[PDB]
Length: 47
Image (cartoon, rainbow, N blue to C red; front, side, top):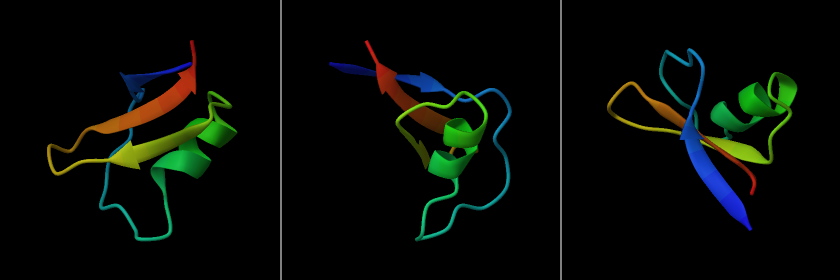
């Protein structure tokens, strides 16, 4: 199973390659991440 939670402080425009993933993957070492138009990013982790 996996859960989604708001990143720590992910800002700036997202890319089609994936910038929210490498972030939460290099920091929180999570599974992946995704950005939104609400200036908020969600990271997926095991739960």
